[PDB]
Amino acid sequence: ANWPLPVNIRRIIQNAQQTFHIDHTKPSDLTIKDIVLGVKDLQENLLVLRGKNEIIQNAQRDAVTLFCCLLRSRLATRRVLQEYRLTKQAFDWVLSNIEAQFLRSVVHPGEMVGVLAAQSIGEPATQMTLKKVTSGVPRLKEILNVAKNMKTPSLTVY
Amino acid sequence: RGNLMGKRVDFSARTVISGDPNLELDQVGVPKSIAKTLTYPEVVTPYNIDRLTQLVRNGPNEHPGAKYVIRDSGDRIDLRYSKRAGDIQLQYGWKVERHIMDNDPVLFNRQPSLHKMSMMAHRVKVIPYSTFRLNLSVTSPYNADFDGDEMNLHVPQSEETRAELSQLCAVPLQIVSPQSNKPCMGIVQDTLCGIRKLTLRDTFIELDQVLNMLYWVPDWDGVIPTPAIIKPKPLWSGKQILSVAIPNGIHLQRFDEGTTLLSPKDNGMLIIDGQIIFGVVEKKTVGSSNGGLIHVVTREKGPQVCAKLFGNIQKVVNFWLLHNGFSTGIGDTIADGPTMREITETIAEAKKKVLDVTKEAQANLLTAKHGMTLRESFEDNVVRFLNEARDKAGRLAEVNLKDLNNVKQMVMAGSKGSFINIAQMSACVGQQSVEGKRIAFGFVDRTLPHFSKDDYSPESKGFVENSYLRGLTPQEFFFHAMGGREGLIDTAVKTAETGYIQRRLVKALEDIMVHYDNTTRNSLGNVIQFIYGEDGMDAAHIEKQSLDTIGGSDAAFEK
Amino acid sequence: TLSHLRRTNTPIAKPRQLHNTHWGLVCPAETPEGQACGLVKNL
Amino acid sequence: SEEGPQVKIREASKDNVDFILSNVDLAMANSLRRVMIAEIPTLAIDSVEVETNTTVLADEFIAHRLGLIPLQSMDIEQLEYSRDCFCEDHCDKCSVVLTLQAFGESESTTNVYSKDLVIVSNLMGRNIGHPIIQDKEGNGVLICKLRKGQELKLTCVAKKGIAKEHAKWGPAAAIEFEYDPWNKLKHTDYWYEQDSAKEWPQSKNCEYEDPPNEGDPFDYKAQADTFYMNVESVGSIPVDQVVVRGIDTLQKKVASILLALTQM
Amino acid sequence: YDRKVPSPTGEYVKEPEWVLETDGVNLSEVMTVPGIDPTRIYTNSFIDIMEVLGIEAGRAALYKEVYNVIASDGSYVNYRHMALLVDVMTTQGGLTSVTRHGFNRSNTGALMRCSFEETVEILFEAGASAELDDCRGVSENVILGQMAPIGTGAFDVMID
Amino acid sequence: ASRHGQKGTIGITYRREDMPFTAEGIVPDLIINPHAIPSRMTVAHLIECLLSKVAALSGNEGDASPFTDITVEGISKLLREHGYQSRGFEVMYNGHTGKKLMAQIFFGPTYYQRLRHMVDDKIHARARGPMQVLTRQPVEGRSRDGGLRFGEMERDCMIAHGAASFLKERLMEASDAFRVHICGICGLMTVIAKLN
Amino acid sequence: EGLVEYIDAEEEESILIAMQPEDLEPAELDVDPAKRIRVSHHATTFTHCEIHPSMILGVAASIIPFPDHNQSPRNTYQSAMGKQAMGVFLTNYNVRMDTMANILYYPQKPLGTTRAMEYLKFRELPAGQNAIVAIACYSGY
Amino acid sequence: SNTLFDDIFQVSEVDPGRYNKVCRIEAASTTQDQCKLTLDINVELFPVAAQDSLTVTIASSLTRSWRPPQAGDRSLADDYDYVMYGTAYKFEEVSKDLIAVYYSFGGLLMRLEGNYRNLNNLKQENAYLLIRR
Amino acid sequence: MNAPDRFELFLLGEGESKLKIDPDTKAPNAVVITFEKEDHTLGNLIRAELLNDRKVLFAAYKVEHPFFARFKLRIQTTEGYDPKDALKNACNSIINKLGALKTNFETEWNLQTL
Amino acid sequence: FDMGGYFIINGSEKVLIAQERSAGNIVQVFKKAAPSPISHVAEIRSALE
Amino acid sequence: LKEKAIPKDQRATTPYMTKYERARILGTRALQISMNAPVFVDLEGETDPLRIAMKELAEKKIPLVIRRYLPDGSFEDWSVEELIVD
Amino acid sequence: MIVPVRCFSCGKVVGDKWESYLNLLQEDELDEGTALSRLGLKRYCCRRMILTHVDLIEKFLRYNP
RNA sequence: AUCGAGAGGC
Ligand SMILES: [Mg+2]
Ligand SMILES: [Zn+2]
Ligand SMILES: [Zn+2]
Ligand SMILES: [Zn+2]
């Protein structure tokens, strides 16, 4: 269930509960139409790429698919009305905050991702120190140097 | 590789480092003499001119000062040797090489530069003594230690350069690590142990302690919190005064082990609107861990609030620890006599198992498991038996160790210490290993000349029954030294191998950047990936999310 | 002074590791951490 | 007698005095201890000029040793800080000038005890600058050892000072502080292997306070007003004068704060 | 191996399963053998997985082994970085080593190429081949001492 | 450094009044963190504290020799005979306030060594300075008042931040920036320039 | 007289040694728990007995106090530190003119010393001071 | 501005949960079989012996910076021997028509369950608790 | 080399008043005073004696850095009661207690015979 | 206390360091690598006394 | 070569300012302010050129255009006023 | 090299003691701890200064110049 | 300037 994705819904939900001081006993101000159509419109509102052409639009949809699944899971009409009582104002605020956080979460153009990736792999390797499998720094050396001959080849059979 | 990719540079400095609890995290304790040597060029403006004049008046030898002045013609004026250090009149557009001053952008670096975190912008804090001085929380990105580690400082020389350092390289900005999608820096050492001790339910603080602690917080509201206990004596929980440091609007939920909402253990953490409801603060709550308080404060409040949060938590917790105190002694390592006798009988039972398996092997009754030598199977069985004995004795010691024992307390806070440390210090260090197996017979069919030939007993093969407290025997000492020698050899070789690995990795991926189309590309233009990370997202912003739809019964999903 | 006057250097299939035959003929502990760890030992 | 802090001196000598500081608040006891350690003025050498040194020891070594030597500072309040008098470098109301000269005439090693030091400055009738001698032999602190054919000659200018500027000017060695010997306040949580009582030795002062009773509950209101102290003197100032001058120095600091308010 | 498999009710539940582990690898022969699931078979060697199952499977295996190396110590690295390295090796047809032969050999700039290893040979062949360097690469600019087209240097700035 | 591998440096110097004190008035010459102890398993440091305390009170030497049947319990028995806690813990009072320290503190004499490493030699700072002739780059070492190397690894670290202008200023104006004249038709710095 | 012999590494392979003279004693329960557990040798036909096990250690390791109770890497580190430790290197230092020399003002013999230290002359020419040390959390420095 | 709830309980059990100064207490309301109370209490300030029966009260008041209460001239609102200040963390329905309220007095934890307090003990920042022996 | 002169710990520098009084911002009837060239010795006593007065609501001292000899005292009092007056009364009470201690100790010492 | 063992060259006390080396005139059998034409090798290092 | 420019309409680059973009704009503005250049924002107790540049960024008063570059070589120009900072 | 004037921990003068202490061990064959107790040193911090001291002055004296 | 050696950090 737990995987790394941008934007934290749980914190936004608690922030809405505290900020607008939601009380549970009052019934909501939100029509079902509003909740469902707003979730769909928000899905249209989170943007990673801006292109008009259909291949870029498909790339955007493919990139945002898993995040949209998370949104649909947490922004469910039964949950939004029952699990955490939500006035209309709080729900619109949640939509706005989700969109803003997502737009902040996009990588900035001009970032040197390759150098950062090399450093990010290198630092834990320096920490590595120490049942017959090639592991750790020797395994990493084999992997990087595309070693034709391996100390511990193996086949797992299912 | 040595004169173009890297080069010696001006405006650089190096010095031994020590840590200031009272120094701010982004601040760096630049010594006064180093500031007297280092110069930043400042063009004279109507806004600054007065200060600049006084600086030139103050002179190069006493700081704040300036070493040189640059005219429009460009002829340098050396304040140290000039008849005109006193009569100077600064025409507009002239340059002053001012000394490095407080709250100036600099770069702080530790020489294993495996991270963007290893070179970070810092704020100048001119200090009397000669050491470079830094906050405790900044050690982790550098991996710095105060055993004698030296660190380097580089001074920007242009406004754009200073702007780049301040706007991108600042310590608060790098608090969340793009690698590992988690914070780099957290609460360490005394602050951590003291935060655990203070957060305990039994810990209560009186009005004097509360009052000074409240003042110690720089951004304190001026409102004394209502005491947790009011009737018999006005008393405050450590959690309340700790909450005073937590910024408002911060909510944290953590459930571990038997984390009932009643939470008898005081386990787990619940924080609402900057106040802690229940729990004991420890490394998971307050460390660099994912879902840590640092992560939340950096993401909602902002980086600056989180840096100030580091400072305030350190100040309060260090004050309370200083007046409460902490220590570690031999008695912490000592365990009960009944526990000791149970440990020694456990070791003896493992020895009996080894002897019986050995005798069965001598009768050839033992059957080899498929794919392994019969001798290989014997070695595996004996090694496992002895490792289990060591672990069991250590666990017995951990049970015996009281809540007052300080090694246990460091472990609970997580500042230093592990199960293995207690096991080896009090019960049994265990069996050492060289190149994978138990110690071999360098001599003929015998590991040491004192042993008889053809002996595979744990004593002959390098299992050290005794503990560090108990005292290693001579033979045990030699075998332990063999193991430690292998450890040092492996360390020395591993550093070089990892350095080569990192250099090759960096050289391969150095050209890779995210272009404006979001395509990851190189100088040739070849697209390594069309969307960076396949989602186009910065990993520091990314956090762990639970997807409820994937799991659960279909009936529960429906309901 | 004494340690320098009692020192051995081995110019250079597992030399660095402490060997059982090194029992009482060299110090198990004394050796310089770094490239020469185990190559240089004290008597 | 007079209401307020009440003292009862259990035992006393010129070097050690032992008392019970009853009916005082803790902050006062701590502050008085700090003032005694640091803030009481005393005369000690702050300048040594060596004309001749044939000793094996270096000059700075001997200068540090000379700084450590104890000298009488009873009338030090009459003496004026060299930074507080108008002397160009030093004068008679600010500094005490001493000279030392020793040659190893004897074939055996000739020692240089602190009794060998003599005064060149004009005293003006104050009990100041006499090296403290507690040795039964009457010889002072052994400054240096001189073989035959070896000599040393120097001049030391002793000045008024405070221990916060250097430890030599400190008048007290080791001050013993104890409160709540039965730990009725529970100010410290004992670390025990099996039982705290057997593991932790009884304090002598424990006998003065009445023993705890197991039945009674902890008194939250109770605070420590009774303190047990022992003061040791190096001899530059007597013990009674040490404690009294510490009291007066602290009250002088407080009065300076009040006067600064009035000026403001 | 303990495994998690959907129960008929839908909740994921334990599925203990017998699994074999072999000292050697001849994958092309092993998958065709009956009694096994050819879909789930895994070779630790990337090169055999790549030759048998194509390059994409090799990319996945490359990542899987790197992740195992990181996870044995308990360390975590985000998918993007390890992935990026895997891509850099995988994109150019086959697995490309992070060595002199492999990644350093490329149409990349001659100065960037010479910065890694075999400096003078690369420069000599560039002189003979009459290669022209676009100077797009960072190391070329660092040698050139000019602001790299990197971060702040990516975008030109002009008056409004 | 201690005799058991415990390296360290002075973070601060504290006067005797500020330092914690025992009831006897004994003040610690040196303060070490507990945290360094559990990770390195330097038990003998603790044992030496105990044995040196017992020896100092006894007026006899302490046998720290290896492979000697000296038990911690026996040394603790002697210490208890001398009126201190067996494990060396001592009640201590905060110097700043005079309040009793909640934790009893491990206090004892321990042999320590002044290592050859002292700050003022290590301290170095250049700003502008002398330059080596062939490279036109800064000279090397404190002794020559040289300039610290900006490592290629450090340069990669800077690239990770993207501060291109800082890298260029560090690598050109700070070290070896130079002006040359070239001709496009030559393509090389064959140009002979009479500037004045 | 033949009471002692010189044995090299290759000659050792034929010989059997006992650590303690007390090993070659008749064998017959109640023991101090704190004493280190020593294996009964279960051996006879000893050719020789070791002079003292502590003789395996070098000069720097013999300086180390209670090395049997510490992990080996720390002992190696300290053995590297004694070379760095300041002290009275020789008595003739005032006569001698070395490029650099450092000497403690008030050298102190250690309170806890090895037996081997006697032959090392460390007590005669020490390199450290027996500082009163407190292990405590204080001021965070 | 007035008392929110009051009852009288008898302590089922007292448990020192690895704490020297604090014991967890579980108690049942006398005269009511539908109401139970768990609460962490500092025993040193107020001894809480088992089988004792204690009066318990929760009031909204009687914010601005806390001040020492003069010499008691400001009227005590507490005949009770023990008093704490806390904020309620969770409100749960044990069963339909049956409520439970979770309070936290700076770390000492309370749970109170019954059906009576439907109109009082609302979620609030302020909830003074007052216990009389 | 870089170390400060020790006299700075007890000697006031150029242009440095022993007390500087500044109103607290966002806190009513509160003042922060910077005692230069002073240590825990003075601050702890001032704070405790301030606590004994009922009118003082807040009294605390903080040492912003162990390097530097300065300490900050913040005082909050009831309205109409000047914190400066509270400081004066506390200091004077300390002085009277010290004088009484001096007299009682003199009596006790004169009784003592050794 | 000085024990000697060093030479004085140009006023500098230079100490000779011992060199470790494999004994000559010793016969030892060394298995060749598995991918090698020859399975085993016996080596002696013959030097005059 | 000639007129290899994306029209302002149909520009697909991110409207939001990149961190590097803001940093370089602020640095250039701070440099010009430091070299006696006029300031287009009223200053209330600011003397630092960088602080002035930040205030100008809040005003959106800084006249400059960020020329985002693409691998094909085509360039998209966004004025500071068009760009969104967050 | 020579006996410290004062204990670094207390500050109590110890320069008076040394010679007597030596004579006390030689004259009456005292135990070193008993000699320390007679010399007025009852605290281990000041005691270490007399026990741990090795008087290197004597060797320095033996050198003729 | 080279060469060589020793030490410090991870
Ligand atoms: Mg380190
Ligand atoms: Zn004068
Ligand atoms: Zn041409
Ligand atoms: Zn002493």
Image (tube, coloured by chain):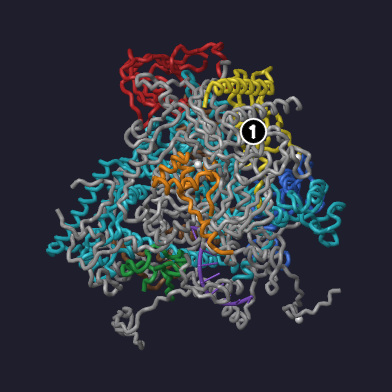
Where is C39 relative to G61, above or below? below
Q: Residue at x 37, y 33 (%)?
A: D200
Q: Nearer the viewer, residue B107 or H43?
A: H43
Q: Which chain is green?
A: C
Q: Which chain is cyan?
A: B
**Chain M tint as drawn:** purple
Instruction: In the displayed orientation, state which residue is furthest to the front.
Output: D106
**Residue A17 position in % (x across, y down):** 52, 31
The answer for which chain carries disc 1 is D
**Residue H116 position in % (x across, y down):** 39, 16
Name the residue type under label 1: Met
Q: Which chain is red?
A: H
Q: Which chain is brown?
A: A
**Chain L tint as drawn:** orange
Read off the residue under disc 1.
D74
Where is F87 relative to G100, above or below? above
Q: Which chain is blue?
A: K
